Image (tube, grey):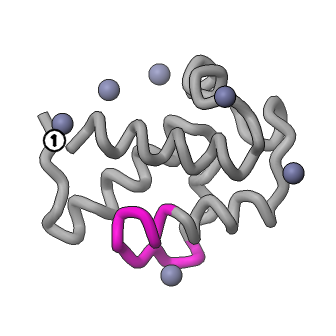
Amino acid sequence: DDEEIEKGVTSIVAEVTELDEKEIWEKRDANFFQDLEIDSLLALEILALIEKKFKVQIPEEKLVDITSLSATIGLTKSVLAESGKLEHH
Ligand SMILES: [Zn+2]
Ligand SMILES: [Zn+2]
Ligand SMILES: [Zn+2]
Ligand SMILES: [Zn+2]
Ligand SMILES: [Zn+2]
Ligand SMILES: [Zn+2]
């Protein structure tokens, strides 16, 4: 479900970065490491929490595309589609 994925990923990134969910959402097209003070350890932790939340496996190599909230949401959606459990509109 698009909305459920967008809110679940926003919640994860807000928790990891210790920022507000609304403010993260406003900065959804912003670059993670340039603008919102993220590390590689924090991106690894986002990836892990997304795996657990949506009950999916995501290969490590995909840390390449954890570069913005929008990119992370797109990653989650594509990985859900590969698992036959995305309902997109
Ligand atoms: Zn819904
Ligand atoms: Zn949307
Ligand atoms: Zn803290
Ligand atoms: Zn808050
Ligand atoms: Zn956009
Ligand atoms: Zn994994």
Q: Is residue 82 left or right of residue 35?
A: left
**Residue 57 in magenta?**
yes
Q: Work out whether residue 44 can be spotted.
A: yes
Towards the viewer: 31 or 16: 16
Q: Residue at x 50, y 78 (%)?
A: 59
Q: Position of residue 44 (x, y in %)?
A: 69, 67
Q: Which residue is mark 1?
A: 88
Name the residue: 81% across, 47% down: 38
Q: Which quarter of the rendering shows the C terminus? A: top left
Residue 29 visible in the displayed image: no
Does mark 1 have its CB less than 8 Å from ligand 2?
A: no
**What is the crowding at mark 1: few (fewer than 14 residues within 10 Å), some, or many (at least 20)?**
few
Q: Position of residue 80 (x, y in %)?
A: 27, 61
Instruction: State the image coordinates of residue 60 (x, y, percent, origin top left).
Output: 58, 77
Task: Specify the quadrant of the image occupied by residue 22.
Answer: top right
As drawn, is 45 to the left or to the right of 71? Answer: right
Comparing 28 with 3, the one in front is 3
Q: What amino acid is found at the position of numbered circle 1 in the picture?
A: His
Residue 77 is left or right of residue 83, and the answer is: right
Number of numbered callouts drawn: 1
Task: Please report the bounds of the magenta region as a residue range.
Answer: 50-61
Q: Residue 17: percent from the left, percent from the top?
A: 75, 45
